[PDB]
Structures are given as structure tokens and as C-alpha cells.
Length: 461
Ligand SMILES: O=C(c1ccc(Cl)cc1)N1CCSCC1
Ligand SMILES: [Zn+2]
Ligand SMILES: [Zn+2]
Ligand SMILES: [Zn+2]
Image 1 (spheres, rainbow, N blue to C red):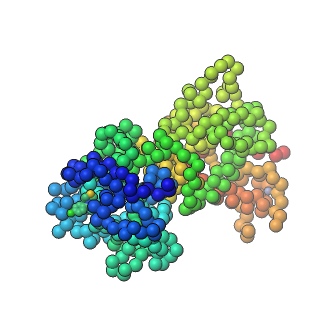
Image 2 (image 1 turned 180 degrees about the horizontal axis):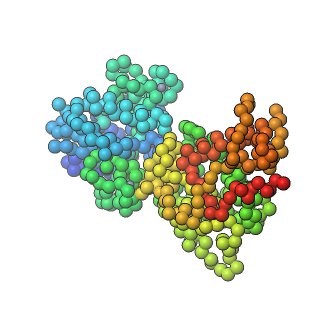
Image 3 (image 1 turned 135 degrees about the vertical axis):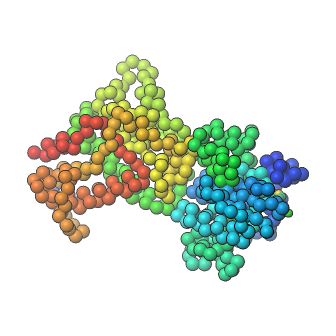
């Protein structure tokens, strides 16, 4: 009970308009056979082209929605749509390409999947709302067999070349013509009523239906992300390191300590209200302040309503207007004016951040976090937090080659005295690096309007 048994039943009702007469009684084994593939009773790490929900959720970085529409089955041209927004027309002889034979279409499919996936995943998972033409199209661009390694590296093979008779991963596949050992999941097997559009549109207003294959491909993946990461949420599932996950997370800890430490020193709040992750620890353990925690899990669907977070259930309940509120990746509709905020910007392009449901994004860094669409109006009571580095640490090198640092934003005794010491120059440059990492990863920082770094210079005298 890890992989999907090929002897599992497959409901064929979705198939029966493209494939009239299809048996009601159907297994994956029989379906794979009718798709023109032979598994040869093979114990070589590829037991089934189709995978479980649980397996798909572990391989979310690999999801490519895929849809095929009859254009006029051997008779007629097929429109191939992918969640990348690409439409290819294959002839048997929003990006929309003219009709070409399979021998050239399959080359474009490998190039497209390789460019999309090489920095994301070791595989492809085709996310289907299966009606028949998508499954019958696979024999024309897919080959299967035993698990293999790349000819040029140690990564599992994802592509095959009929020219060279060799196997490549996504990194090494230029000129390859076949997708090799793809995986796939039919969303329609999950038990929905009515068509794709009617189910997608319950949850999402951002993906229209232009009645083209890529639109269905996008809607199919969106619906799948909704089901697996919005309505259902599993934070136990770990995901491999593929990028700067570790640097970004370190940077996040450093910036959070820096900004909160400086807010307490500058404005001397007697109480801090720490709203969000119930596992959260004091980010400034030495600070004078009354530190009060409020538990809120990461919201995957809609931003929290500040009315419901701060709702008073009895008298003598905490005054959130006293001191300052820390919302560190706690996404709310509208922050109060007395807030310090870190808010993930869902629009950011990275390998960590996958497109999500209804303008949200699926941010995958150790764990998967569906994040509600970034909204600028949430920040109306605040301003953007400007970059600064602050330290009360002694000017003292210890233990890196130097250009003397000149910066208005290096808030240290040494800079107060007109000359930045080597230690604080090294720390400044490391912190500016951490800060830039975190920003470019898509985090945005917001602060109460009265916040002024000028107030920090008098914390040394
Ligand atoms: O792969 C095919 C297929 C095979 C041969 C021919 Cl001539 C047409 C279609 N499918 C999808 C699986 S169910 C039966 C149709
Ligand atoms: Zn390789
Ligand atoms: Zn959608
Ligand atoms: Zn110094």
C-alpha cells in the first residue's frame, strides 16, 4: 500500500463521450493496455503510469495539467493544452501554435517540459480531467520501461531519443523526442458531480474558460491544487531542497530578529502581540516587553478577517491597540496601524513558488503552503519597512577582505562616531545579503507609520 495497484478500478463514465462503448468495469491494467502501453509484469520501479493522491501531493512540483480537444482520432487534428499555457495542434498527416505532425510536436513537448521542470522535479505528473483524447494521445509522445538514469548524469531519466537510442533527465534532454516514464492522475476519479468548469469556478475567479485546451489544463491543475492544498492541508509532508530554501529561512530569522528588536528600541512598546504560528518562539528573547502569543495556523484559502482574529469572547480580553502587533506571515484582510508585518507576495516568480488557486500561490519550502493572493489594500494603515542594519554589539573584529563601508543605513556606535569598524561592515554586508535574499524570495515587510530609524541613534550615548 505505497503505489497505486494496476488492479484498482477506474471509473470510465468521463471517457464514454470520446470513447463510446467503453466497459463500465475497468482496471488501470486494462486502461494502460488500451492506451497502447505494455508493462510486461515488470518489477523495475515503474509499477503504474497512474499514481495515488498521496503520491501526487509529494510530487506537486511535477504537476502539469494536460488536456486534449478534438479539432475537427486518426481522422482529425488534436489540440494539446498544458498548464504552461501552451497549445500545440498535432495532425496525423494563451499561446496557440499551427498544426504539425507528431514527429515535430513530440520534440516541442520534451523541450517545454524540460525547461518548465528541470529546476522543480525529477519527474512529470500529468494532471488530467480525463475524457479520452488525452489518454489516446500519449502513445504518440510517451515511451515507458524500467527506471533508468540520465546518459550524462545520476538523475533519473525523463526523456528518450529515437535518434541516439539514449535517456536523459530534464537538464540533458536537448534534441530528445519522447517523454519517458511520465506519471499521471485523473482528477475525475476523485468523485465530483458535473463538469470541470462548474467544479473549478466554485473555488476560483482568476482562470477563465476561453474554450481552448490550455484553459482546461490550467483549470484541472487549479482544481487539483484546491483539493490537495486549500480544502485539505498536510504540513507533515517534507519536500526536497531544490534552491535557496536554507539561506531564505535563515535570512527570515535574521530580518525578523533585526526589525522587531529595532521597533522595541525605537518606540519602547510595553506589550507585543505575536499573532500566527502556534509553534512561534520570542524572536527577541532579551527585549524588555510583555510578549503575548495568539495561535493562528497559516490560512490556505482566504486571508483571516482581523474582526475574527481580534474578536473579544469575554471582558478583560487583550487590548490589541496597546503596544504593537507582530504578524510574521500571518495573512489578514487589513492590518491594524500598530503592526510589524511580513507578508509573502504570491505574484513572485521562483522555483519555490508554484501557481495556485484564485490568485493564491503554492509556496513549497520544506513544507507546502497555499497562500491567499497578495492584496495591497491589506497594508493601508502601514508603510513599507525601509532597509536598515542596527547593532549594539561591540566594535571588535575577532578570528574576509575589506573596502571601508559608507552607508547612512548602518546604525552602529562606529558609524555614529563617523567611521564604520571592520566587524560592523562585515555584519552589515552579510545582513544586506540575507535581506535581499528574503525580498527576492517574495517576502514584503510593512511597519507602523511612526517607525523612524533616527530614534535608534540614541540607544548608544
Ligand atoms: O489509446 C487509446 C486508443 C488506442 C487505439 C486506438 Cl485505434 C484508439 C485509441 N485509447 C485510450 C484508452 S481507452 C481506448 C482508447
Ligand atoms: Zn542528466
Ligand atoms: Zn483556477
Ligand atoms: Zn563597529
